Length: 537
Ligand SMILES: OC[C@H]1O[C@@H](O[C@H]2[C@H](O)[C@H](O)[C@H](O)O[C@@H]2CO)[C@@H](O)[C@@H](O)[C@@H]1O
Ligand SMILES: [Mg+2]
Image (cartoon, helix red, strand yellow):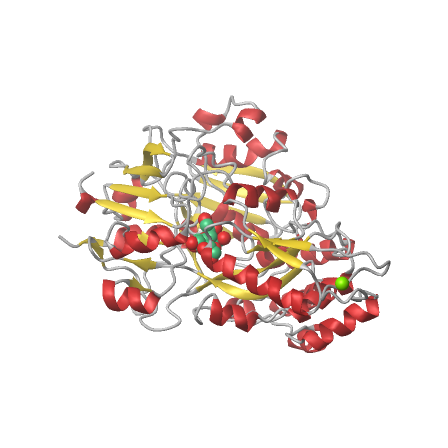
């Protein structure tokens, strides 16, 4: 590969490339959604604004009707026109194939009418405004002419090698350590939008540890990093590395990192025991030791520190029911529960005098999180809870997470920047996790609460700020009381870039895109990074 025509990117590939199935983004190579398959809309989180992508236009034309207008001249990478047929199919395939993640949309979407050649009217039986916003940016459009005779088992389990999407890149090749994306010269976006991605190839690289990426970035072997990297001041000073902010904290906030708790494991089943753990943990020690202040500690509700979310901040609820770092309070609660260290080994036993210990886990190689769960474990040990950190490889970590096979688990997959605070509370409480074996959408510890479901629906169905503020407070109160998830800090939108080959990266001063290619972020304008960068030579 001609080096000056190629973009080396990493930070999102933590298992060997083997799946490009748009229906299973948890297993698909990052960029499957974004580079290959495309959404109806982008959402710009910096300005809280939707940007029509495959759609030309979309709007609510009544309380329960949403009219979508598709652009003309859209085409699949194989030459076949992309039309409203494909959008209808993308939704209707999940009617019979209930195993598809968004099959439940048909509980509140009633039908999709064909208005004209490229216009659809979505008619809703139950207008869930908040979740619809997320569906508009996250649902990839798939080609009817390819998927329409696939069995449900194929739809859900097929690797989908050499995926046929509509996007600006297709898959050229792949191996244990990489997926090579090649530019689609016929991408509809070039003619219709005037957007021309500059890299001829994007090599998505896999490493076994963040530490490996350091030397690659130092030597200009990596162009675009979405790895957490330590020692950023030295990277910038000595290797000309660029970041979003010129100075500290260097990094945008991306999501809420916190601990999901297995509520079916004694004594993690005890709500007050989970509250004790919350009081025990010192997020500032993580902020300084793991991140050298590139992140900030989370408010107790875990609400991202962003105007779109914080206008609903339940200050009175947090003042009343919130937790903070206070080991005295944690120990008070533990003593009241009867968890006492009778045998004087520093570890509390349960009420029957039986010793117990727990694990906390993160992916191996995620170096900042390894340090973070060491810190968390040590805090818990300081109040007599025997907790040991464990570092499964990413694949085992993910299976532990999705299947709810853990004691404590550090995660941030579902608490990311979005068009609605509903996605946060859904990421925490996702009711369907309880009776499903695997959950990919949140509530990974399978916390059950019938009251919470009704409140999520209330929030979902509202478009009035006063009502939204009201429901957010009720949801936050239950979060703070039962703590199925303990919010600790806002993890960074890790971005550093080398200018050895590519320049004009987006920055605070020139915020033309959010330069993040993790799955979920291409549609949060990560894709627009590719149109702005310039080949130095
Ligand atoms: O900071 C922890 C690691 O995050 C990784 O990116 C994650 C990201 O934080 C979130 O979990 C996401 O959407 O999945 C990503 C991986 O595909 C890497 O940046 C890694 O280097 C960090 O150690
Ligand atoms: Mg003891």
